[PDB]
Amino acid sequence: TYTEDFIKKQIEEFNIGKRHLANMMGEDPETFTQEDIDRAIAYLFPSGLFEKRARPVMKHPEQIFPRQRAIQWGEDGRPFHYLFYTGKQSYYSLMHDVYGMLLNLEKHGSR
Amino acid sequence: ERGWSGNSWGGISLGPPDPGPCGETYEDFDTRILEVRNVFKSIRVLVAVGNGKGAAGFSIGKATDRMDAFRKAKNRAVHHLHYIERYEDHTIFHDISLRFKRTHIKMKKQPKGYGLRCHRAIITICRLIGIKDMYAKVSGSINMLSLTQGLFRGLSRQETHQQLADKKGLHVVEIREECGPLPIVVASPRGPLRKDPEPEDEVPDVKLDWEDVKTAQGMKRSVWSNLKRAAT
Amino acid sequence: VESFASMLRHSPLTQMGPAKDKLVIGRIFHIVENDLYIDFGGKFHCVCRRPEVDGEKYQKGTRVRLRLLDLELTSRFLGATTDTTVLEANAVLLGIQE
Amino acid sequence: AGSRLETVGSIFSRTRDLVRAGVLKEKPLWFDVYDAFPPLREPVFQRPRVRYGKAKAPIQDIWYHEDRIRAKFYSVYGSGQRAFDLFNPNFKSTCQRFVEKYTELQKLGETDEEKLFVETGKALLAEGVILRR
Amino acid sequence: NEDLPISMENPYKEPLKKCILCGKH
Amino acid sequence: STDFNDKILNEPLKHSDFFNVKELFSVRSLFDARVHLGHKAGCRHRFMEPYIFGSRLDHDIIDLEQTATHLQLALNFTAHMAYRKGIILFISRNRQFSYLIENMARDCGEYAHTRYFRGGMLTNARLLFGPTVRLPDLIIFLHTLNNIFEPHVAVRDAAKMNIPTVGIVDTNCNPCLITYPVPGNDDSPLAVHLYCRLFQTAITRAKEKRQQVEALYRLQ
Ligand code: FES
Ligand SMILES: [Mg+2]
Ligand SMILES: [Mg+2]
């Protein structure tokens, strides 16, 4: 599991590496872009591997590092969502919203 | 140290219960194995826990491995605790006669220094509870689970002196032979006190047990009764 | 201060007596295709079918005339120690209250 | 965490025994509120029992004097063609008018049930209420 | 209180149903 | 923190009605909401007999004088719990009022569970929510029965987890394990709306009073 500090350090390292690559390839660091990153990394590290993922890649850290650390309550322990104890707060909240819309309407190529 | 016998699991201590998911520690609790049985293979264990101050419980744990069964039983027991009222923190408040299924248990309150003259499992459970003086007789089927269940029900359903005083609205006065005719008030009603005395029942319609009477009158001749035994 | 006994004694529901074959005024409060849910002042609502005659006039909030048959439909069944209730009243829809 | 023996005592007695025994470090948030304002009955589990023999429920049937009048009214003039409005807290049915007139005549005259009924019918017809037997 | 209910037999009790030959020889 | 405790958490417990919940309802209001209308005598539960005024043409009538005292106690308990920032969970399996109860819970800043109750919400909460989940301090049953006319499992589970319960109990319900039962009609929409209104008002007033007392104590 990756802590926020780890991702922060990866962000700083990525910025420094971006400037280093821009210096290496002779472009201006200020205007150096991610498409430029891809082109430069492909040139400096040629790779014929068919799997585009397998080929060497330099990306912004968050694009690889996934995150599903959704915390559902605070320090006091009170859950944020009023449907928390159902265990399916998002689904039942959506169902509740749809039911309310249907009540309002009753008062009044694709898949 | 051995249990009730050299090769028996019963009476063996399992140590304190593990710290719970709730975040509570139980270093003041002791665990004792009451039964281990092969289930046809897996193992079913009956264990009891208690802190020696009235908080006690029991549980069944089933698992393929014996140690897993011990752990499950102990952890479940700590979360199903009874509180047992003790008279002067050494005995029960009154005589208790109970029947759970086919197992009959007859317990007698005793003075200090009497010790635990009870079935070995009852001795273990009493040590876990903190009862130090009591007599007990088990009759009918001697089934360990039924014995434990009946014992815990009977000990959890005992009426304290304060409860009796509040119920009858009267002083509960204790007469001790060692203290002469001095009246010792052990409980007084919290609310108002009735001015009318209890009916002086000429002969109460109490259900007597033939064993107690026969022992009192001296016709009990058992060679197994009142035998010298190690301190319990 | 009016006691509960007085309110019960002078209540219209208490005054109605037996509910069998009594004409009442109910209000439609829910529509499910051709199912009309009507409140008439009782504990339970009654569900009626939309009449084939002037069925468009039966809408939410409409006042209707009903013949009550039972305030709550219950019945004890074989091998049961308590009655089974459908949580519904029985009534016949007569028409719209003019 | 507390004892999960919901059939022994109540939540209050279990919690109190555990707290005084030192098992629980702190009282739960509701313990003090329960102390200050206890319920009328302590919530102790009890197993409902089927009645047998001569035991009967102590629930009585709610009857009033005028019910008799109502019954016989409903047996003679039948159910009024007028419709009851139970939503109105002060609805007044034809039968209720008959009852009030019957009681008025009872307190202003003698006690003869048939005579009271016929006289009340005459009075209602005089007032202008239709009553088909 | 005078508004309390009072004990009586059910006045709305419908008569028990009879067969077509009830009371006939 | 001793002064904080004594002035904020212990002070409200010295008054019989600290939040003035008695002015929120009257026997007249309960009668007008049809709170006294129970089920037929064939559906009666034995433990509900002391709360029944009588049977009117085989329909049980709930004694509203007792309902008033029971509701006073239940509302007082709810208000005191909300003042102490306790988690309050409303539970009801009557689908006719699921939307209303969820709206009410969202409005008063409390929690609702009107859906299928999965085995182990309360007795197995650590596994199903997380090791540090906080359970409700109070559970309020608008309907204590499930759709098969048996007790809501949450009643027994709350008793197991030592969570006090307030509950609306009709004539066919079992009030033995509910900490603060309130005898009343649980079927008519008027009665349910009244219950929701009363509980919402009590909770919001208690929370406002807590904030006001905090502000006054901080100022002085
Ligand atoms: S009912 Fe048959 S003889 Fe009367
Ligand atoms: Mg040996
Ligand atoms: Mg109901």
Image: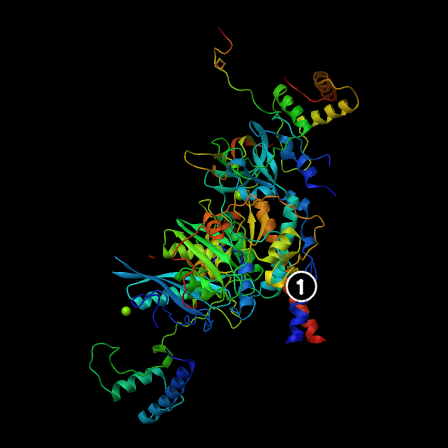
Q: Is residue A20 left or right of residue D44?
A: left
Report the coloring of the rendering: rainbow
Q: Position of residue F183 (x, y in %)?
A: 59, 46
Question: Looking at the image, which is closer to me, A97 or F201?
Answer: F201
Image quarter for residue F7? bottom right
Spot occupied by residue B6 in the image (x, y as percentages of width and height): 30, 68
Residue visible at 20% across and 80% down in the picture: A49
Q: Estimate the x, y position of residue D119 in percent, counting from the top left.
A: 73, 17
Residue closest to the eye, B169 or F121: B169
Q: Is residue F124 visible?
A: no
Image mark 1: chain: F
Q: Is residue D54 above or below residue F73?
A: above
Residue for point 70% across, 61% down: F15
Q: Position of residue D17 (x, y in %)?
A: 54, 63
Element assignment for label 1: helix
User: Which of these two is toward me, D133 or C93?
Assistant: D133
The number of numbered badges drawn on the structure is 1
Please tell me which residue lies in front, A38 or D126.
D126
Amino acid type at mark 1:
Leu
Can I make out residue B5 in this image? yes
Q: Determine which residue is flagged by label 1.
A: F13
> From what the image shows, is residue F131 above or below residue C23?
below
| Residue at x-position 51% and y-position 64% | B54
